[PDB]
Structures are given as structure tokens and as C-alpha cells.
Length: 223
Ligand SMILES: N=C(N)c1ccc(Br)cc1
Ligand SMILES: [Ca+2]
Image 1: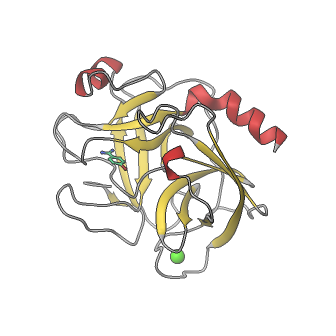
Image 2: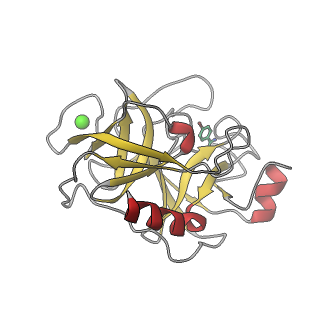
């Protein structure tokens, strides 16, 4: 997260870290046994880390649970990043509390102008690299479809939306991949891609979760 603020320990209780010996992606807890992330975060041997603030220090509220199964969306296209969403089933159910909690799926799609919360442990600089150890937060609005398509001609599908600031300076970044975009208490987006980070006229692009609720519910019910 570039240009954000320190969230505060366990103030984003649905945020997960995906760990394969090191943090490599974010995710969102959607019930006690399932996590949603980006398909471009796929790999084998994932450990899901819940209840994290400082990802380099054991602070006492963590739960570490291995993944038993990962399911990439059947239509994910790694060249265009269309359908950039994946589900991860935990080997055992998390213990839910005030600091580890699930986030609700949306019943409708959020409109442009809605303010949302984006969070992650990704790069905090738009040039160079500096990775924080504690969770960062950013409040940002959803942008109109026309501004999004004007920023990225020929690249925005119906399964993507833009959020952020056309002036630059505030954005998600590498390492935030797969993490949540939460608006009005519902999961509306997944950190997916962008051109650089926090560049002028290049806002972040997010997977449009409301298009996938039926696939998520059917998949969870059968696996
Ligand atoms: N929002 C961005 N600018 C961005 C997000 C994820 C990745 Br990976 C790269 C860039
Ligand atoms: Ca920790």
C-alpha cells in the first residue's frame, strides 16, 4: 500500500496472509474454512496465516492453517487477468473471534463513488521498494467505468473495476495482490493489477467479486 496508514493491530479481522516460507499474497476469510484470493497468487504448499498484524513477529492472536485444496476460477486468463479469483480451503476450521472474523459476500455490486477500504502488506513506495511488517490500510473510492476504461484502453473487462485516485500517490502495490477491497462491510474487490503503483492516471484494477458470488457459493457447497 502506497500512501496509506497503519491500520492498527487486528482492526481488519478478515485479512489473511498467504505464506510459502514468506508472505507472498493477501486474501480474505469468507467463512471458517474458506479464503478468497487472486488466481495470480496460485501456488502449491500454501499456509494461511490469520490474525496477523506484524507478519515477522508472533504477537499472540495468530492462527496458522495449511491449505488442503486450491480452486482457480475455470476461466482465469493469465495474460489478460480476466477472472482473477481463486478459492482456498483450509485443512481445519479457523476459530472465529473479534480479531479473526469472516467478511460477508455482496448481494449487489457497488457503484462508482462508493468509498472502500483496501489493506495489505505490500510495497509502500512508488519508486524503489520498502516492505512494511505491519498491516497498511487505504481508503479509496470506486471509479466510474468510463474513467477506468480511459486509463487502460482495451484492457478492462466486465469483471474488473478501478479504484483509487487519478492524481496518483495512493494505491495498492506488489505484495498486496489477492487482498480485500471492502465497501459498506461487504467484500467487493480483490487486489489484481495495475501499471506500476500510485502513478498518475493509472489507478488500481480489482476483480469484481459481485460477479462471482454464485460460483463461490456453489463451489463451497460441494467441496
Ligand atoms: N494497484 C496497483 N497499482 C497494483 C496492484 C497489484 C500489483 Br501485483 C501491481 C500493481
Ligand atoms: Ca504475527
